Image (tube, rainbow, N blue to C red):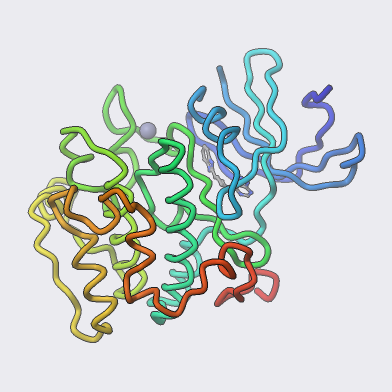
Amino acid sequence: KIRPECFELLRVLGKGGYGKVFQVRKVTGANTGKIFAMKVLKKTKAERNILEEVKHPFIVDLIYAFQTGGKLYLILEYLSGGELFMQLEREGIFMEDTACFYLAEISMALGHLHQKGIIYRDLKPENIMLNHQGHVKLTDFGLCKESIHDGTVTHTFCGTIEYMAPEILMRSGHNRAVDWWSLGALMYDMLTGAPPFTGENRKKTIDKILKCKLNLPPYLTQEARDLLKKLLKRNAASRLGAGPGDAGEVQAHPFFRHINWEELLARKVEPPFKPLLQ
Ligand SMILES: c1ccc2[nH]c(C3CCN(c4ncnc5[nH]ncc45)CC3)nc2c1
Ligand SMILES: [Zn+2]
């Protein structure tokens, strides 16, 4: 019988209009002393269902869920490695082997989601956590983490849209192909220092993304350039990964040729950065 009193609050991990996340310590039971992330929501149904349905090394684990008063409590594994964002921000630009590692782990997580009919939509690097070893954990399954909200209804444009596919921005209907686009935008950000389509303002940024005139930096390897070219396409159906082979298609691309997927999945590959050493 789990209740809020079973946990002590340690610090705030994040707050927005639609929930708050705490680092907490369990103080009862066999897991006495163990550290978790606690998300509290004001009652969302998709979020819980998603987290209960997925089980994968590169996706955050849900340990407990319960509702007391009007609040929903989600107890997740505590991820101490921070946001992928912070590594990018410190490094400026990743070496290709660095980028390859992260993108490869993300692709497996995306594959798992898609098999469960789940679409991640937004792979901006603040939406990817690292665990204590430095491996990827997809975490962003909730409504919106913002405090100021675009549109008096839906939460597509609240944060940056720089990693979202044209067809999402147009609201013209979409599928799992948007995730492969977003993987490309993230990849582009890793290898060049900024997402592919940026404007002086929101309106300009939308227009650039819709026009999708890709600038392939010449200093990248041919494999990296070819993958970016095949991910960042306005025609969703014709992106790598958009076909029946999904993640398998992307993982077969020459940019990932040095990846042992079995070793990757089992997390036996050493991450480029170790959060414990930071
Ligand atoms: C509303 C407003 C701001 C928010 N910031 C989040 C983030 C916060 C950091 N996250 C985690 N950190 C550590 N262990 C974690 N385990 N699981 C997640 C997690 C990831 C989510 N969710 C929000 C909801
Ligand atoms: Zn919002």
